[PDB]
Image 1: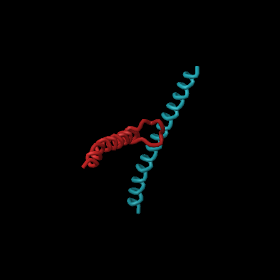
Image 2 (image 1 turned 90 degrees about the horizontal axis):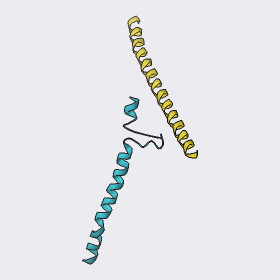
Image 3 (image 1 turned 90 degrees about the vertical axis):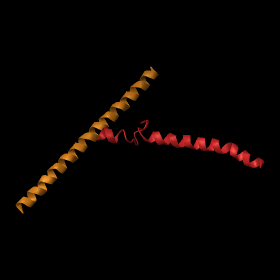
Image 4 (image 1 turned 45 degrees about the vertical axis):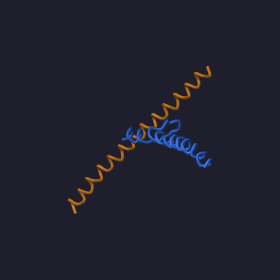
Amino acid sequence: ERKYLELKSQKNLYLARLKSAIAAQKIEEIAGNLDNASASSLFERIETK
Amino acid sequence: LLERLLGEMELELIELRRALAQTIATFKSTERQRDAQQLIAQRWYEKAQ
């Protein structure tokens, strides 16, 4: 009964970190920072079109 | 065969036109990239000065 709440006290932190990490690359995809011109999306296809 | 070949050529002309358009597009894009690169070089020169 002790160990269970021990783990429950960190489930949330892990979920938060994971969601932040996902969101990072999520908007890094759209409108790349163009630090390198290797690939940019949705702001170059539109520009080229 | 006359009308057949003329229709074929009619299609092929606009195909060629589209291809040349795309060529002009990336030529402009490459020029823009060159300008950005030389601008960054100039900025680093300013920092050095």
